[PDB]
Image 1 (cartoon, each protein chain N blue to C red):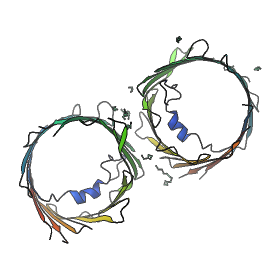
Image 2: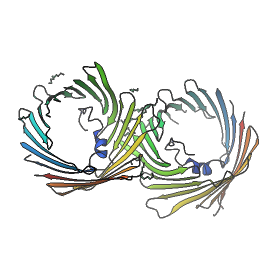
Image 3: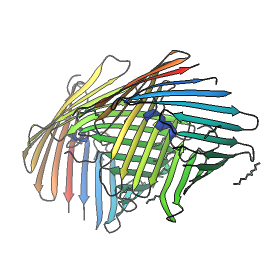
Image 4: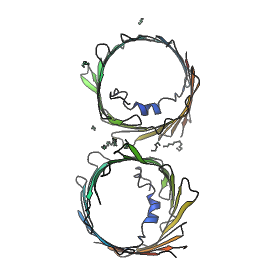
Length: 271
Length: 278
Ligand SMILES: CCCCCCCCCCCC
Ligand SMILES: CCCCCCCCCCCC
Ligand SMILES: CCCCCCCCCC
Ligand SMILES: CCCCCCCCCC
Ligand SMILES: CCCCCCCC
Ligand SMILES: CCCCCC
Ligand SMILES: CCCCCC
Ligand SMILES: CCCCCC
Ligand SMILES: CCCCCC
């Protein structure tokens, strides 16, 4: 983040998360194709490694910009269809509201106002409410979030986050429902290498969990990622854009200490 | 030993270091007077090469009920030093101190915030200096005896990173192997092994990027009796080092040392030390 606008609470510490999460894709062979990116068509076909289950997905996205609207369609192989309507920066400079639906309810309305040093958020779920608030002060970041159930009239979760970040170095911490502590350090050495460190421990248990990850970019269109943790789990991640259109991702998981591993492959056609 | 908590970054490879550093004290005659709640530790040392004399008066008193520790430092030259330490009050593994000192020499203060835990050992340093404030972080992880540590010093005056140090090592009480890289151009390794209760061994390794030559050292500590021990060290720079320490009675220990320039007639050094404990 190089702007004066703080990210959303859910997007807090995304840089370190991208080092651990993205670039791997274990235990799934998925084939995705997005086109006409404008009417945005997106096809997704993922096959499972453990259960050998093949599930498909076809996504359409009508987006026309001047009035700030974006329609969304997503139907999967086993019928479950949802629509998403979102207007951006029309009723106010930093206003944004969405509308959700599903098919066999799960309708949702999500409102969020962003400004310089401030990024509030509120979500209406159909019957719970989730409110979020993130404040930025000279590179620092503080955040709070509360999920409220309307029927029980009781707060479900309460997360409080503090952190400091730049485009080169990020540190974030958060407490989930009071009993869960989590921390993540992200530091990029150069344009070609990225490295993140993860920390988490639950209140009431003395033990903790830590993990390290890497993201090494050899060529502009070929990079490598590797992660590990104290649970004797290893993860390798490879990616090579074969040509501008198609982009291949091969990865593997190794169980350091029965003896079942995981292997992942991914192709990303783009026309 | 092999406690669940990893050590401080600066404390990585302390078992090997102690075989070299402690038990010697060359070229200095020192007299320490430790006294027990509060603690008044009086120190008086005289240099052998320049015949200068310094005497330090230290006052410390801890408060176990609230984890507080007060510490005062003052020497012959009018230099004052103060330190306050709180432990395990705001959190279980939390610890944070505040140092303050000035010398009629410069004046500076710093706050050192460090959180140790099972398998973790976090530590941060907020240092306010005359030149510029300096922020120094340190994280050390432990996985089944393996230790991986990192440390950075950040000169905040104008955004720059002063030193970056990456260190890995496998540590058990019977065998401690450690390696570190400093500033990306300096490498250093230590091999600590204790043969038995009576003998300890350490090996030192060091070489700099851009120079073919290396520097190594071998040390040893042999403890003849419960009240007497012997030390020895030698490096590839032709420097022999001996030391003898004997507890004469419960409250006193005597330390004799000598540094002998092995090859090329150079100035030799001799050390003597007393440690009254009362
Ligand atoms: C923190 C480093 C984790 C390394 C784990 C790799 C798995 C191999 C470990 C074999 C002993 C359990
Ligand atoms: C770096 C953050 C350190 C915060 C300490 C949290 C305390 C964890 C709970 C342990 C029992 C009090
Ligand atoms: C020029 C920006 C005007 C901002 C008004 C929007 C207020 C949203 C209140 C939550
Ligand atoms: C663990 C302490 C976190 C403080 C980070 C220091 C960043 C300030 C640089 C201006
Ligand atoms: C964990 C942060 C250590 C301080 C480094 C600050 C660099 C801006
Ligand atoms: C525009 C078609 C909407 C279908 C959603 C039920
Ligand atoms: C500053 C918020 C931390 C809460 C600890 C229970
Ligand atoms: C507890 C964090 C201290 C860092 C001061 C900037
Ligand atoms: C704590 C050492 C691992 C951090 C990435 C170099």
